[PDB]
Length: 52
Length: 87
Image 1 (spheres, rainbow over the protein chains, first blue to last red):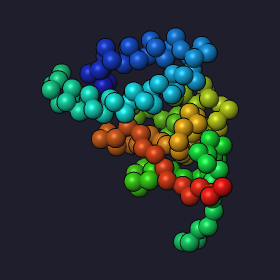
Image 2 (tube, chains in turn brown, green):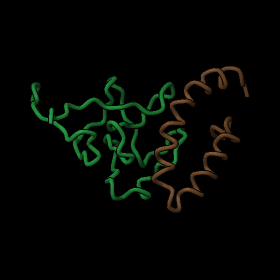
Image 3 (tube, chains in turn blue, purple):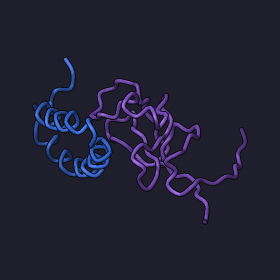
């Protein structure tokens, strides 16, 4: 197995990345940059609370 | 090569091709074409124009300053501190 703990989160981000990969890749790369910094705030308590 | 280096970069440095695989925190950078368990969609093949190779710090977003992914699960990506020109 692999790290599939954030299956829903990864899927959402992937679907967005795939859709934006067309031409909005420039925006996608910037959006993820500002969103991942927020992920550190969410995943901090999220990953801690969620055991599985 | 030497201990006391003297150089400068152009603002953000989106055209930075310098060789460095460490963050400003002295953390080891992960290879762009690697497959450690990370969450990302930055495939080098998607941005061949930014010359993403090995585990060298790059900036495909053209943001404030170059960054890179870390090989430490405690961190995702960190920025790199490089001396920039005054003007």
